[PDB]
């Protein structure tokens, strides 16, 4: 005490409260291991037209009532169109005011953003050290078709620096993805995992991957979340 602290970044169409509810199992284990888990809300307030999937008026009202019409950034299928400035500043401001944080945990948009923040934390928040641990749940990077490599993807130029990982990072990366996930197919999370693995010269003790059988969700099954939490707590020691 003060005990280690992790910052949790939710996914598209959630908020801090809902993410806390969805991550209750992992949070229970971390709290038992004397780790503090902080949840914050994404700043981009969505209108119905900003949804990339169908939803009726009733379900949209329900979304409004729950205060979950939120994103870290507007969705686009075209990576060069993405703008993370507001969401990034929101998290950075929070860390400035409430840090330092020993680690970070992100889901889907929150995981794309948490990965970028992991890469850049010491530049974004002067005097803040590297994270000890970064947990990337159903994450992805801002890829596009590679013109000279049909069928292959590259990171869009706007975000090349953002997803660049320096060699010899102290941070332990923990990737989590669901085998059934169709919102963010695991190929995207593995693509991002590979960037870290390469930067760490193939060291699977520093860059870890856990696949669960489920879909686009924070996993809760004992046999998956226990080893994950063990890896987090061991990095914090
Ligand atoms: P992530 O969940 O933040 O990004 C993936 C999609 O844009 C969001 C999504 O499929 C949903 O929010 C589904 C409910």
Image (spheres, rainbow, N blue to C red):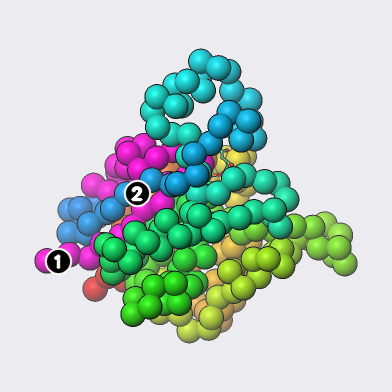
Q: Is residue 124 magenta?
A: no
Residue underneath mark 2: 40
Q: Ligand 1, what quadrant?
A: top right
Between discs 2 and 1, the one toward the N terminus: 1
- Most extreme residue toward the left is 1
**In-front residue for pair 83/3:** 83
Up the image or down, 83 lies above or below 44; here it is below
Element type at mark 1: loop
Point out residue 119 in the picture as x, y percentages from the top left corner. Answer: 49, 72
Q: Quadrant where the C terminus lies?
A: bottom left
Crowding near the residue tagged with mark 2, few <14, some 14–19, many ≥20 C-alpha atoms within 10 Å: some
Q: Looking at the rendering, which quadrant does residue 135 occupy?
A: bottom left
Q: Residue at x 48, y 34 (%)?
A: 69
Residue 172 visible: yes
Q: Is residue 27 magenta?
A: yes
Element type at mark 2: strand
**Residues drawn in magenta:** 1-28
């Amino acid at each position: 005490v003060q005990i280690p602290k992790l910052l949790f970044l939710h996914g598209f169409l959630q908020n801090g409260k809902v993410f806390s509810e969805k991550s209750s199992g992992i949070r229970k284990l971390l709290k038992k291991a004397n780790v503090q888990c902080d949840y914050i809300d994404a700043p981009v307030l969505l209108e119905k037209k900003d949804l990339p999937f169908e939803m009726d008026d009733e379900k949209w009202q329900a979304t409004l009532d729950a205060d979950v019409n939120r994103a870290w950034f507007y969705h686009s299928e075209i990576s060069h169109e993405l703008d993370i400035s507001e969401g990034l500043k929101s998290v950075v401001d929070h860390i400035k005011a409430n840090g330092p944080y020993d680690g970070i945990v992100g889901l889907s948009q929150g995981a794309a953003l948490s990965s970028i923040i992991t890469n850049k934390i010491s530049e974004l928040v002067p005097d803040h050290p590297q994270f000890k641990v970064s947990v990337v749940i159903s994450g992805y990077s801002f890829t596009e078709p590679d013109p000279e490599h049909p069928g292959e993807l590259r990171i869009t130029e706007k975000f090349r620096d953002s997803f660049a990982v320096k060699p010899d990072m102290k941070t332990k990366m923990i990737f989590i993805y669901g085998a059934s996930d169709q919102a963010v197919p695991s190929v995207r999370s593995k693509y991002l995992y590979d960037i870290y693995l390469k930067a760490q010269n193939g060291n699977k003790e520093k860059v870890l991957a856990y696949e669960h059988p489920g879909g686009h969700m924070v996993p809760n099954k004992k046999d998956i979340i226990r080893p994950i939490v063990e890896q987090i707590t061991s990095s914090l020691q």
